[PDB]
Length: 55
Length: 430
Ligand SMILES: Cc1cc2nc3c(=O)[nH]c(=O)nc-3n(C[C@H](O)[C@H](O)[C@H](O)COP(=O)(O)O)c2cc1C
Ligand code: SF4
Image 1 (cartoon, helix red, strand yellow):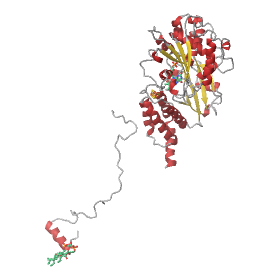
Image 2: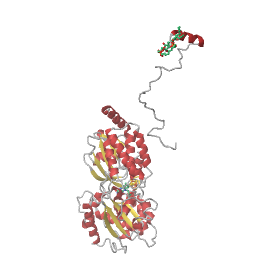
Image 3: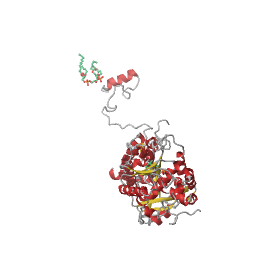
Image 4: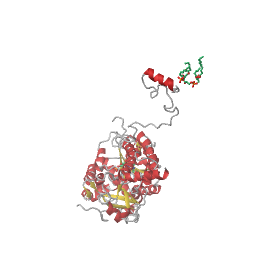
């Protein structure tokens, strides 16, 4: 997405498609590599009552 | 008869309960005791067992087992080994201070009970396992037993019947678990007071390996009075299968705490408002009543309206009676702190033998120590219930049951008070 408009237009003509809307090279649109700390939920049997394992 | 209570003074078995009369033997024959004992001893064990089975006497120590069927397990011939009637006198039950009154004020009645009960099953000798903390009662009882030996009433040729019979007194050393019958048997033998497993029952193998009946002071001391006054007289009181009289111990937030004898099926409201002078602040100030000592689940003010203080009506009140100790708790009482202190009692008085009591009582006390402050979340209420339902019925004796039962009663009758306690913890500490 650094190509100038002449090469960009020639490339859109030779492909016959619209390429700058769907780029395969990734840019700032991706998630950030440093993520917030997660807090995952627990399973449904993490309960202090009615936790008899035979049931 | 359907109206019970208001027992007359002429039908009281326990004359000189308060200490206003002479407790010694010349004062004991002035109150009817040690009278016509030879004609009791010469009618055989079977007439005595029949007069106990006719009387409808049940257990007075915390069990409620019938007395005559209990003593009839020991009506078997010997095979070289003797038999022993041991009287449980430990009385570690919180609320219950009645056998202390029987030992301190009517000791000759207890010795006559030992003699007649040992005649009733062919026992060789008697052991009175008195509490170690009752040292004044122990010396009181030993002076009375000396006066019993120095008249020819017990010992060699007891009351002129050719039936040899000793009476011993063994003192405890400060263990509530020695109140239970098998741990009392283990405490006489000179070991750690850790309860035995049934079977073998004490009626087959009890103390020292001899057949032994451990019976409470109250259910022993009234049986010569049953044999003299009449079994139909003693079964004429109370409701059906709930006969007799009972020494009630009304303590706590009453105006006048008292040990007082009353007919078995007396209403609790009538008992408190007559013999104790009412709850502090009145009956409108009544929050809860621990009905029969520490091992019974408490009942709130709506249950204390109509309930009868015998075994079957408290079973219908989904609680127990036991030793009939009325611990009264008014509205000014922090109920959670009281039950947590009672669970602290049950962890400082528990012998530590098997795993469910040894772990669950300490773990319930930690949960109750968080519940008093409120340091929990409400989903730990029913979980604690399951903790009680993992103790109740999986132990050796009924101290695990007696420690699970107060927490069950507290939760089952005061759950929303615990929930508001923990939500106000949540708002004022976070
Ligand atoms: C934890 C526990 C403590 C007990 N403490 C006493 C006691 O202090 N005094 C007593 O007479 N019975 C006590 N008992 C009841 C005895 O096990 C037994 O029932 C009693 O010695 C004789 O029963 P009886 O009432 O038929 O005579 C206790 C039971 C348990 C489970
Ligand atoms: S449950 Fe408790 S009181 Fe009973 S034998 Fe075990 S340690 Fe003793």
